[PDB]
Image (tube, coloured by chain):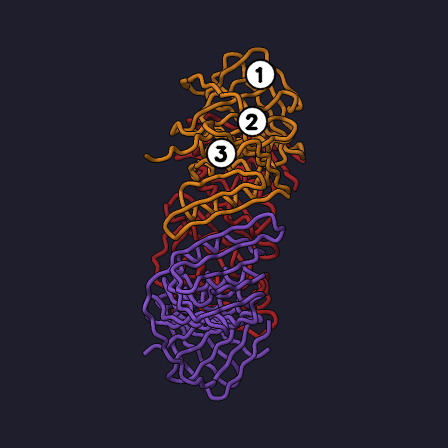
Chain colours: A purple, B orange, C red
């Protein structure tokens, strides 16, 4: 048996909202420590990793580890049927085949029960090398989303430069060019251990900022020659992290 | 002759909003007791009936019965020109041809006058079978609209099964299946005099829920072998009722 | 060297929003008295004129007159990158080629710098139409926008009839007709020096009401024989005026 009860169900809604634009299907790895999901995006450019610890659920039981193949488009459509204050319960039998989602309204007079067919996917885990923290930028998540949206009107790629005084986002295109300079202060903190200057495709960052509702801050972790990490904390539960390799 | 003054003009706006998605044209029957309208949908699947009693109007005068053929799209375009707090007056001369709508703002500095051409429509007598109240469900109108929208993501048809303790709405499709169970308590009341289980096309129920702004509650009246009634009360005036035949089973 | 600092940058955002539906490219004429723009719209029916006087800017310096050819679509995209409370500075070197727009948040922790390529345009050469103030109506801008939208559901043109006590807006089409009567009082004032009854295309007036955010009042200046003026004041700075001919003449 697998059964997990989450009183703040909107978390799951926001999680699915943050993944379906990027991934069509993926494996949810369920174990006694909680829920882990790792997947390349459907264009095989970026990597996504989700962690939800068992301690963040109001009830959690996992008799046997399972790897559930899920069409995220379908699961997101089902989670649109939950109200933002619903209690959400996931349940799956040993040897999978279907996953049940139960939404209990807080009045207690209405209960919704959805059953989703599970898919047959063979995906193997990619390893994540140890992180080098050359620059770490923590900033309001809405400000980062607006930065990416603004510069994608100028160009298709952003140059992120992190040096002692601050962090700069630059783009260049047919209409001209732009840059946005942030200095350390809705607080902005900058840990610069060695300067970095890297180029990234704005299309993928604009996908990553769909996780903005999960947290009021985002963390950017940059180092030379390794993927940028864009990370959102899922309070008292885990994280959603996106990895993106720099250009050229 | 005909003249009716309605101080809460937004009612008419909401009425037209609730009809234009289902029917294009309809005959407004005007008499001294008030306004009646009945029409099948443009696909002749569902039926709509509207009553606005003369007593719900602040002024009401009708010297001779009229059957006004109205393009509901045009009437809706005109009523979009009224503000939500406008006083709305309808006026028509004996033997019709046009309907006048006057919108008076509450400031009193602005008055709008619209004249709408009427049209010639074929009217087919339709009878309503007396209602059998096998199951009656009263619930918040917003909750019913959300139930219908949620399950139309799962499938195109909803099975409504009504039993002693409660009512269940079920759907099935690709993606899988879902059901939503309501128990008696934003109050939900369930009168089950005999069990009913019927299937209905979610597309038409989704048309019916465009009436949600007229009332905070909706009533579902279900019986075996007779069309479902989905009813919204128009407080202190009348009602909008929608009728939908169940889907026919296979074999 | 041209440099202009505007502490209420949202003015510039609203201006570009009020022009971009109507004009793709136009010349911004910069002089020591300020910023002037005039252009026919992209369909060559209506005329648009913008004035922003130097005194309205908190800083203003113009060493030499410039004619900056600007793609207004590009400029509006850049100005969407400014927040509504940003301080905006425009800057251009002598002999143009690019225009710099600097957006400073008021906390001072964020600064955005955009460089926009200018273009060489062959301007049409236009006079500003003659004025006669036969009738002048001042009214809330939102009410005027609502009148134009509502009647464009009835017909393609509005007949504006002006009398001493009030003004009437009428339209007619295949579904029927409508009129909206305003009397002099969110006040509407009417200076009627000669009676007027004039017809104008609602499609173009509906373009003009995109300037509604710049002002809570709009002024209609009507005459037989010269173009209607629809005017929005840009408070303590200038105006945006739209012109439409009453007749084909």
Q: CA separation, marks 3 and 1?
A: 41 Å
Question: Looking at the image, do the residues carrying marks 2 and 3 touch, with CB atoms under 8 Å apart?
Answer: no
Image position of B46 with respect to C43: above or below: above
Residue linked to disc 2: B113
Between disc 1 and disc 2, the foreground one is 1
Q: Earlier in the sequence, mark 1 or mark 2?
A: 1
Q: How many discs appear?
A: 3
Q: Chain of mark 2?
A: B
Between disc 3 and disc 1, the foreground one is 1
Do pointers 2 and 3 mark residues of a single chain? no
Residue linked to disc 3: C224
Residue linked to disc 1: B2
Image position of A103 with respect to B107: above or below: below
> Is C149 on the left-hand or right-hand side of B191?
left
Decide which of C65, C107 is in the foreground and name it: C107
Q: CA separation, marks 1 and 2?
A: 16 Å
């Amino acid at each position: 048996m697998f059964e997990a009860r989450l009183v703040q169900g909107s978390i799951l809604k926001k999680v699915l909202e943050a993944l379906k634009d990027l991934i069509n299907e993926a494996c949810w790895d369920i174990s006694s420590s909680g829920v882990n999901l790792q997947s390349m995006d459907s264009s095989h450019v970026s990597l996504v990793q989700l962690t939800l610890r068992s301690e963040g659920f109001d009830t959690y039981r996992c008799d046997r580890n399972l790897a559930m193949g899920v069409n995220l488009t379908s699961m997101s459509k089902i989670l649109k049927c939950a109200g933002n204050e619903d209690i959400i319960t996931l349940r799956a039998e040993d040897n999978a085949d279907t996953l049940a989602l139960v939404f209990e309204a807080p009045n207690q007079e209405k209960v919704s029960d959805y059953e989703m067919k599970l898919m047959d996917l063979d995906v193997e885990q990619l390893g994540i090398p140890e992180q080098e923290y050359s620059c770490v930028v923590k900033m309001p998540s809405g400000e980062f989303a607006r930065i990416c949206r603004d510069l994608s009107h100028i160009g298709d790629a952003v140059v992120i430069s992190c040096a002692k005084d601050g962090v700069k986002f630059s783009a260049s295109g047919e209409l001209g060019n732009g840059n946005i300079k942030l200095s350390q202060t809705e607080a902005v903190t900058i840990e610069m251990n060695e300067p970095v200057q890297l180029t990234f495709a704005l299309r993928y960052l604009n996908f990553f900022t769909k996780a903005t509702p999960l947290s009021s801050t985002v963390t950017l972790i940059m180092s030379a020659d390794v993927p940028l990490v864009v990370e959102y904390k899922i309070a008292d539960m885990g994280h959603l992290k996106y990895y993106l390799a720099p250009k050229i």
